[PDB]
Length: 49
DNA sequence: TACAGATCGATTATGCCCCAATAACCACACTCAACCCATGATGTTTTTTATAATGGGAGCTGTCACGGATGCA
Image (cartoon, rainbow, N blue to C red; front, side, top):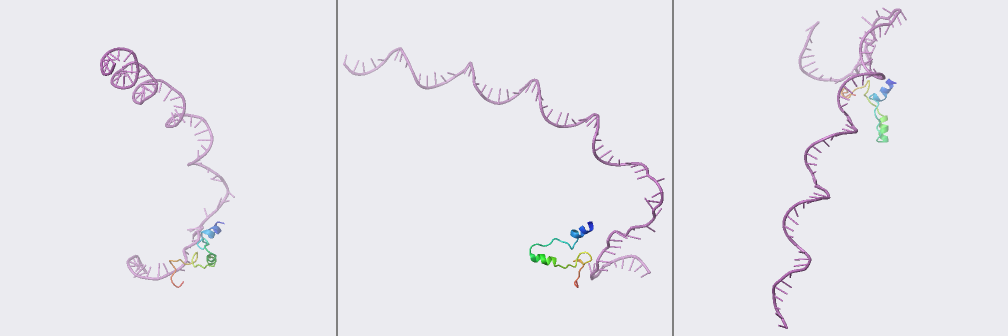
């Protein structure tokens, strides 16, 4: 339960869901990110990615 | 006959003993703290356990790319 709770809420890929519009809802749930565990960082990422 | 005054008798002044309050000054007091010294309940620390136990890595870290030294071999 500790590990699953840390992933659900304390991880980078789980963040508060935007609720301004239904469009914001859809475009936040249909989102692809290249960060988080095993991914790049904004400082590290160059140009090709 | 015309014209005068003259004493009874009234409002006004000026001062003070009392005195019905005025204020300071001095006398005695109860209640409420303050600190202390216990009794004891709670708290904190120390000591010992005898079948046998004999080498983790803890999660790596996930990957940019310059320059300038730098310590070698």
